[PDB]
Amino acid sequence: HWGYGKHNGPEHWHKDFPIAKGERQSPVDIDTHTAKYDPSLKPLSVSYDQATSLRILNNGHAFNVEFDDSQDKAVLKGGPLDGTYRLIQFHFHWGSLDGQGSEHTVDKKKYAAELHLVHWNTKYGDFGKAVQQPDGLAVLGIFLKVGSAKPGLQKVVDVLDSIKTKGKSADFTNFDPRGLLPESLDYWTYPGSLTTPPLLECVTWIVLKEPISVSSEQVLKFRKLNFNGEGEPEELMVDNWRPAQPLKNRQIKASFK
Ligand SMILES: [N]S(=O)(=O)[C][C][C][C][C][C]C1234B567B89%10B%11%12%13B85%14B%1158B%12%11%15B%139%12B%1061B%12%112C5%153B%14874
Ligand SMILES: [Zn+2]
Image 1 (cartoon, rainbow, N blue to C red):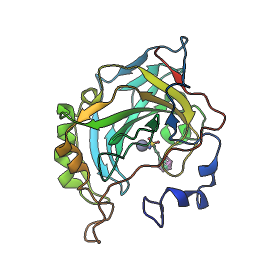
Image 2 (cartoon, rainbow, N blue to C red; image 1 turned 90 degrees about the vertical axis):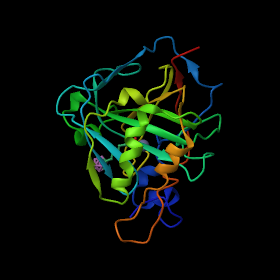
Image 3 (cartoon, protein in one colour; image 1 turned 180 degrees about the horizontal axis):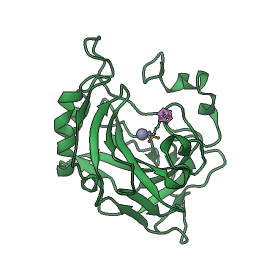
Image 4 (cartoon, rainbow, N blue to C red; image 1 turned 30 degrees about the vertical axis):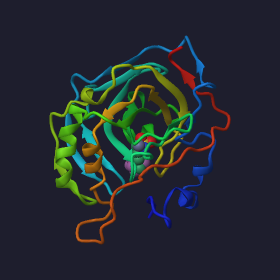
């Protein structure tokens, strides 16, 4: 099955998922000097006050913090988006060392990690239908750098020991994702894809310019997770990022001057 090793990693994915070589793949490098300021872009509206987290799951590739998406409770709108996108889950991608881990890059800079808040367009009724549409998902991407601790992340960090291995989950209620946001909602946006198989070309990407800071100790705990299942040979869950893909016939737009 696909993963992030030598034998099953990103360079192999195209064999099972030929869209890996498609026209709107993610992530990409954001060349800051080429991205054009678009004064028509709106402020992003992030409405997470009623977000209801339920559970955290180690799926063998990352961990997902899952939300109740059976009503409009936590939604993303505005920015480049038409209509309303409901939060379903967030997860991260990270490295074995602080010098790599992000999926998007900024002028070729790699951050230590990248947070993805995944939302689906309510006009398609369910997530599985949304991923079949070119405007089905909106993913809000946030870079992580290592420095000061992020207090709002610590609840996530502290539950990771209970979901060490693939297929483990834990109750994870009352977690407030507002504590993971940077001060500024300035962003870049472009049309792209899921960064994991099946690599579907269904995503409007919204990547915040301002990173969040997390501590070395926080990211070190991400790196103690396992890709393997319980009792199997330990493979640390590190370097679970896809590298930048060709931009092809796409424009990255900036919300800010
Ligand atoms: N890293 S990222 O933020 O670009 C991607 C986040 C969303 C990935 C969704 C994957 C599937 B869900 B539905 B089905 B189940 B199985 B098939 B279909 B969607 B694709 C897979 B699972
Ligand atoms: Zn992701």
